[PDB]
Image 1: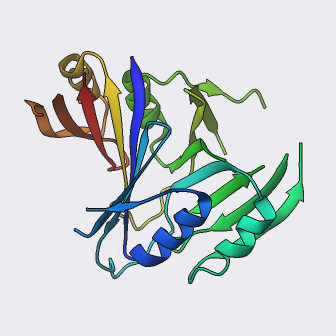
Image 2 (image 1 turned 120 degrees about the horizontal axis):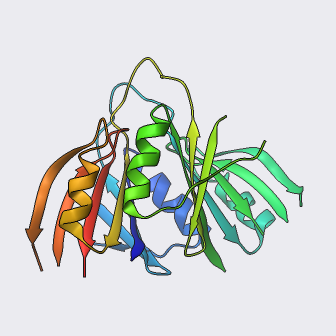
Length: 110
Length: 113
């Protein structure tokens, strides 16, 4: 009786976020300037908005399970605005935390 | 090779957000030992963390979308949660649809099929 059907993020860094989430594994289709990827029945969309002129650290955190954690992290830090906060570490499950261009803490697991 | 495994929202309205997302359909378990509540639905873990009032409240960048049963009845219950308000009333579309605001100010889209 419940389905999560869409996650939407309004971003002033569309190109950086597109680059970021392509590396994670999303395949976006272009149609605000809007790009939509659909993965496992969930629609992940990115909307272009203007610089809010008071930049806040976001309340949203996301978690993904991926293959090639170390190789993915290497590619993600090549995206402008993105930085690794927790390096790939063996945990109880290899884990890394990386920041997207909007400042979301993205947790990655292999 | 890709799974979305968790959505986490850090909120200063924990009680209102818990009330809101229970009505949507999430079953939250509090931790045994931030104040944190976690629900897990279809392989995705939806967590709510209690944080303090940021003192400069921003309209959030996140919008969520859900498919539910009893759209009109759900919306009726959601506007009974403090801070929540309906911005688009239940409307027949190409698929009955409504948009409601959560206590944090996220625009939540709701559909019935």
